[PDB]
Image 1 (cartoon, rainbow over the protein chains, first blue to last red):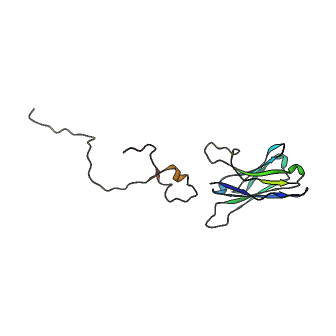
Image 2: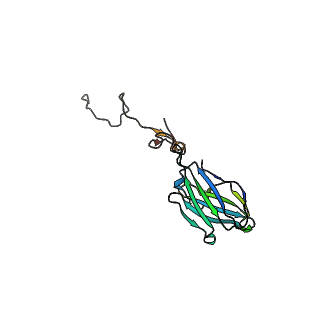
Image 3: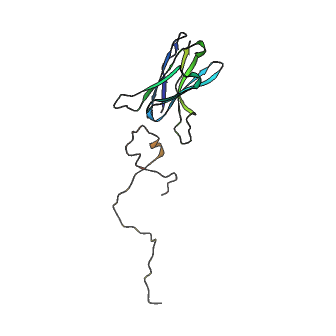
Length: 128
Length: 53
């Protein structure tokens, strides 16, 4: 079973950067993109970007470019080599960035596209 | 009429005891097990949805 586990909630001061981790397991980590999305109070969901774990290629929402950086680390455990961690760092925070941040992954069926997110991390609340 | 003639039959229900290489069958949930774990479930052909004996 696919599992995405994020790092805990944090309080950040304006001007700070926050680095959120998403430990992904139960599937081959290199085979699926991870997206990040934020749910903002009174504004709804905002897609942040995606990362493809093989080369770590990335794409960032135009309106957030310059403030977001996504990276990943692949398991270094010889008997458990297929999981990995995705990281998203979000900088120059303001109170308007107070939101719940999710890492998400698509379904693995034949008609599953890139954006329907079947799997969700438990979310990370960031209060600025 | 007294004279009989042999006529050959194809599809006659009869068998001789044998030995031969058989092959494996397993079900879809075995491949849903994923995790690269089960042995030879992958190379193994599937089963029948409506088996008949």
